[PDB]
Image (tube, grey):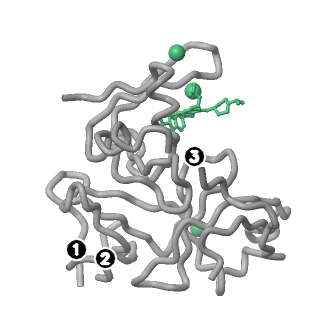
């Protein structure tokens, strides 16, 4: 399949202009093989697209350049998984800000990258956390998969993955959006989610 490949495609919403995108295919979701998780070059979120049916996608092409294959410190990486973190980053004005979040897993395909999410935006992100850590920007603090989900806004989706390191945490793909939403099912954020 196209997992592990780099791809490029056009994107058009409605009568808007076509924009061009390059990225890396990370995963073909077991519970919905039409759904691919993609990391676009320079964009930090993980996106899910049903490439075989999404008419917003045009001119889909496999790129001839290979994904970097190739971690510098697998043991350090291992220890980050499941940890609460404070993640500092540089802002438009040159000052730094920080978001607190949780390291979820090593990313597939892109070896040096990690899945992470944040209280301020609880969707799936990917960063090279060992690079950010070495530069002093990362402080480490001391089955439902395949089921349908709804919440009242009726927003509908599917549970696509369970986080091994924190089994009450799941990834959800909603039908109306291309982000991957992350929820800890014991928390308030998840209290309007119901499953079938
Ligand atoms: C924008 O957030 C981050 C950018 C990062 C980021 N940018 C770079 C921007 C400038 N460079 C140059 C080459 C042109 C290219 C890449 N580089 C890195 N780590 C490599 C550098 N290191 C090791 C010194 N890490 C980053 C971590 C970020 O945020 C973590 C918390 C989650 N965010 C999501 C978010 C969304 C909207 C508002 C705010 C946030 C906060
Ligand atoms: Cl930064
Ligand atoms: Na620094
Ligand atoms: Na959408």
Q: Nearer the viewer, residue 87 or 11?
A: 87
Residue 178 appears at what percent x and percent y? 55, 65
Category of crowding for the residue at label 1, using alpha-carbon neighbours closer than 10 angstroms: few (below 14), some (14–19), many (at least 20):
few
Q: CA distance from mark 3 to mark 2?
A: 25 Å
Q: Which residue is mark 2?
A: 149
Q: Residues within 10 Å of mark 2 (few under 14, many from 20)?
A: some
Front position among marks 3 and 2 = 3
CA gap, disc 1 and disc 2? 6 Å
Q: Is mark 3 within 8 Å of ligand 1?
A: yes
Q: Position of residue 73 (x, y in %)?
A: 43, 38
Q: Work out whether 33 lies above or below 152.
A: below
Decide: is 13 above or below 142: below
Query: Which residue lies under the disc numbered 1?
Result: 194
- Location of the N terminus by quadrant is bottom right
Residue extending farthest left = 186
Q: How crowded is the residue under tag 3: few (<14 C-alpha within 10 Å), some, or many (20+)?
A: few
Quarter of the rendering containing residue 99: top left
Q: SS class of the residue under badge 3?
A: loop
Dot 1 and dot 2 residues touching (CB under 8 Å): yes
At x 25% / y 68%, what residue is drawn?
A: 193
């Amino acid at each position: 399949n196209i997992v592990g490949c780099r791809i490029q495609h056009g994107w058009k919403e409605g009568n808007g202009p076509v924009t061009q995108w390059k990225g890396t295919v990370l995963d073909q979701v077991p519970v919905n093989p039409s759904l691919y998780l993609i990391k676009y070059d320079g964009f930090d979120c993980v996106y899910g697209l049903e490439l075989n049916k999404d008419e917003r996608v045009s001119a889909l092409e496999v790129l001839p350049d290979r994904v970097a294959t190739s971690i510098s410190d697998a043991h350090l990486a291992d220890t980050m998984i499941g940890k609460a973190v404070e993640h500092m980053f540089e802002t438009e004005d040159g000052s730094k800000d920080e978001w607190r979040g949780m390291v979820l897993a090593r990313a597939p395909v892109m070896n040096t990258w990690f899945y992470i999410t944040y209280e301020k935006d609880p969707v799936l992100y990917m960063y090279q956390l060992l690079d950010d850590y070495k530069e002093g920007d990362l402080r480490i603090m001391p089955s439902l998969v395949g089921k349908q989900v709804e919440y009242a806004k009726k927003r509908t989706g599917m549970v696509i993955h369970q986080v091994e390191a924190k089994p009450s945490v799941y990834f959800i793909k909603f039908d109306d959006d291309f982000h991957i939403y992350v929820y800890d099912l014991v928390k308030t954020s998840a209290e309007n989610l119901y499953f079938q």
